[PDB]
Amino acid sequence: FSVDGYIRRAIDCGFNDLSQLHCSYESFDVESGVYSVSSFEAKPSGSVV
Amino acid sequence: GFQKCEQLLREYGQFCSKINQALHGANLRQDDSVRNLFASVKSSQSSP
Amino acid sequence: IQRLDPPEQDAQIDRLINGRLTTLNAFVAQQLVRSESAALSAQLAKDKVNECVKAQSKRSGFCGQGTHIVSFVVNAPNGLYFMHVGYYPSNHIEVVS
Amino acid sequence: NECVKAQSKRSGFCGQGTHIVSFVVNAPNGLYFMHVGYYPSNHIEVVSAYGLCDAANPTNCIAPVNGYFIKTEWSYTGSSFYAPEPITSLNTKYVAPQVTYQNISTNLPPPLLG
Amino acid sequence: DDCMQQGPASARDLICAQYVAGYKVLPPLMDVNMEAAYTSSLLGSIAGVGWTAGLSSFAAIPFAQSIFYRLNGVGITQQVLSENQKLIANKFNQALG
Amino acid sequence: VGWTAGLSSFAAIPFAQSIFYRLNGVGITQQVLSENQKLIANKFNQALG
Amino acid sequence: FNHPIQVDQLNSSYFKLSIPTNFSFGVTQEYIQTTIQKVTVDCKQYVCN
Ligand SMILES: *[C@@H]1O[C@H](CO)[C@@H](O[C@@H]2O[C@H](CO)[C@@H](O[C@@H]3O[C@H](CO)[C@@H](O)[C@H](O[C@H]4O[C@H](CO)[C@@H](O)[C@H](O)[C@@H]4O)[C@@H]3O)[C@H](O)[C@H]2NC(C)=O)[C@H](O)[C@H]1NC(C)=O
Ligand SMILES: *[C@@H]1O[C@H](CO)[C@@H](O)[C@H](O)[C@H]1NC(C)=O
Ligand SMILES: *[C@@H]1O[C@H](CO)[C@@H](O)[C@H](O)[C@H]1NC(C)=O
């Protein structure tokens, strides 16, 4: 949010792992490093009943 | 000693096992600390 | 138990459980912090006996203040009480060397 | 730095006994120190001097270096192992005279034969 | 039993609380006489341990003799220590007294 | 490394030679170390073995 | 209580020396932990699955 309140820039926090990093620090600029982020989930391919 | 409570306590997992083990280890730590400390204060030779 | 039936009795007992579990976790966390601290401190005591008491130290400020001469040790309620005897100069004068 | 890269003179810092040499290997969550110390045994009691002075020349006195002057007349032994050897200029230092030094008048060691 | 036949010593008696609250204070690893034995043997080792090279031999020398070597070792000459032995002992005694 | 003054020079000397200096430095005389070099090495070896 | 060797003081200008006649080498073993296992947690997955 700019001083005048408009949104000029944003991060989609679920787009990729880099985006998740920015969101977790609530910043567009984070320091260099190696960070753990949410795992890449396995998803169901079907169901058994 | 209330059974209803104990029944509900069980749903929190082995809570008390964790309390007891953590303190048991913490208590062993002092016996080991003391044993080591005194082993080092101990003199080989000394005058009366 | 005497006042309430199970659907509400449960909620009330559960509040007491949560509070007591919290208390015990806090207690244990502190016994672990305090025992870790005491253990480090015990190693300091070990070093002082060897450096201070069983030897004359040349390390300024390790034992007592001033120049170390001799130290003694007695037991204390939760540890050791060190008695460091140092040499304290006074009435300094200036000379040319 | 104290143990492995150096011989330590700090009692109990490294291992027990008198430190000689230490080695290090890795361990699962850290280092495993291997401290080799010198452990004395079979101690005996002998009679020692604080120092020796020439009885004829009382201001000429010696003290042992890293050892003791022992009766056996007087001889020198290293501090960690009883093994009498002659008192020589290599195991003595000249010192100011003291009331506790012995006055020797016969078998004067070479540092006092002046 | 003390907490039953006499009861709590005062308000908030944490020793008697043990049998009520559900906690126990455990005894220390060594009794008092053993700890005293360790520091007593330590006292008797001081003069003869901090004396010369190596940690293997013991010089059973007077405490006073040890002090004078300790003072000489920090820069007080032997002529001074010899003239002032009674003064030094008195100052030492004042420091501890 | 544990041989003389300063941390800047390295004396590439035998381990055994280092041990004898270390023993001499704690109060065992050279006459003793010289007579007992094999005894000393054997005791050292027993300690590690 | 394991008593130390008692060495008497003398009423004289001499002193008693309790000195070794024998020796051995021994090894004091010591372990120093320098690290702990490094763990990260996917907190969102842990809590909500
Ligand atoms: C080996 O020989 C030495 C040298 O003779 C001997 O040590 C000397 O012993 C005498 C006493 O036998 C000391 O002389 C005096 O002793 C009294 C004892 O109370 C002191 O009070 C005296 O001090 C006063 O006088 C001094 C004179 O200058 C003053 O300076 C001082 O401030 C006091 O006023 C005095 O010490 C003598 O000093 C010592 N010598 C040394 C170097 O200390 C030694 O005992 C003999 N060895 C053995 C084992 O007998
Ligand atoms: C022996 O010890 C007593 C203890 O008071 C002392 O007064 C006396 O002078 C001592 N004798 C010697 C030779 O030191
Ligand atoms: C030193 O102790 C060992 C222990 O067995 C013994 O075999 C050896 O003969 C001893 N040496 C002396 C000089 O007593």
Image (cartoon, helix red, strand yellow):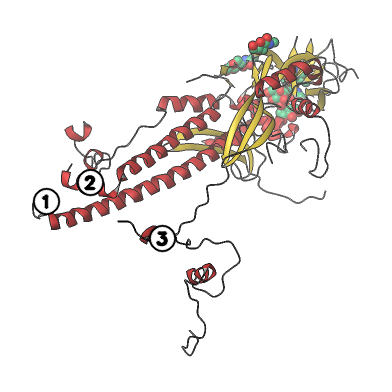
Residue G21 locus on image (x, y percent): 69, 14
F30 or C54, which lies in front? Answer: F30
In the picture, the disc for residue G45 is: 3
Q: Of circles 3 and 2, which is in front?
A: 3
At 75% from the left and 9% from the top, the residue drawn is D72
At 81% from the left and 37% from the top, the residue drawn is F4
Few, some or many residues within 10 Å of mark 3 (<14, 14–19, 20+): few
Which residue does the numbered mark 1 point to in the structure image? C1
Quadrant of the rendered structure where residue D25 is? Answer: top right
Q: Secondary structure at mark 1?
A: loop
Which residue does the numbered mark 2 point to in the structure image? E11
In the picture, the disc for residue C15 is: none
Q: Amino acid at mark 3?
A: Gln
| Mark 3 vs mark 2, CA separation in Å | 49 Å
Chain letter of the residue carrying label 1:
C
At 56% from the left and 34% from the top, the residue drawn is C49
